[PDB]
Image (cartoon, rainbow, N blue to C red; front, side):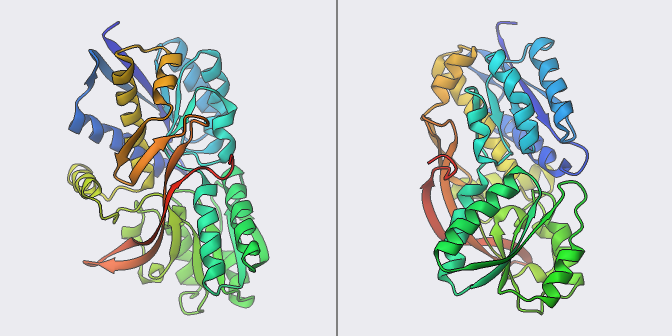
Amino acid sequence: AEDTFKVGLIVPMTGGQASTGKQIDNAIKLYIKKHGDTVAGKKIEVILKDDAAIPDNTKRLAQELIVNDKVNVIAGFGITPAALAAAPLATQAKVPEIVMAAGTSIITERSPYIVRTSFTLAQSSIIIGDWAAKNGIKKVATLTSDYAPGNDALAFFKERFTAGGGEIVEEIKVPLANPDFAPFLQRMKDAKPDAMFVFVPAGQGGNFMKQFAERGLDKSGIKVIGPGDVMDDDLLNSMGDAALGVVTAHMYSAAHPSAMNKEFVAAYKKEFGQRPGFMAVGGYDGIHLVFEALKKTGGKADGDSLIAAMKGMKWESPRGPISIDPETRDIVQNIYIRKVEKVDGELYNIEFAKFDAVKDPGKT
């Protein structure tokens, strides 16, 4: 048992956010295919548990992994409440909690053992806020999922956009579970703002765009902006021409021109027959952090040693250069602005702007 290192992966494999857990599970499989399953004399075992994005299930499964399976690390957490539900047990058992998906700013402050490899909504939202203001968009209506990351997206977009002389004319919120976009989009057809600012979690953008095109807003001259979540690369292949010209700020694009991303995407497509999205890259880097931490401690598997090793650690990711902030345990990464274009018959988020090494604005 001393030659074994266990990772308890708690992600949604079923339900609304199933696409998140599918991507993270896949990326981790690929990382192991490409790097092996052994570091510092320890055989890594990933134990997968489907919480179906229900926080009550996340707590039960995290307790079951830590106490019964005696995992060294817990990872994943598709939504913010899933991450928050597991934080007390991570703190009590001194087990690192690797947040590979959830994007609310405060998450890292809720446990000293939390480290994040995904993003915060504030990171992207401040950038699209500034861009919209500087690009002649004056009147914006917002649609944001009615929970923590959506509130973060809205608050940070609003702050930067209004400081640039923009006006928010309407604020609309929809549930995380089975949102209906029709009423808001009908409101958009009558009251016509310059753009809509839209946040919906990974896996939902396809449904938004489907209803967007059905209400014919593609011709209305209302631009679509926001953080990249709506323009999920896992979903872009299914979207029609209405998505063309949608401008988002985000930390990852499948079209990121780097050699490592070229290699990552090709390998992902070959192995799974699908384009990887931003959730996949969150898992891929989450498990890299686990591998590289064990290497740096020389096999020491206790929580304190791992966290200390994880802090300040920097590497190149398919998304670009990233690092774990030694002070906050949150991810410091580039934020890009992208435009949806068609290349070789496929829609891509094409990066045209780059902001270097953005710390979470929710903590700065």
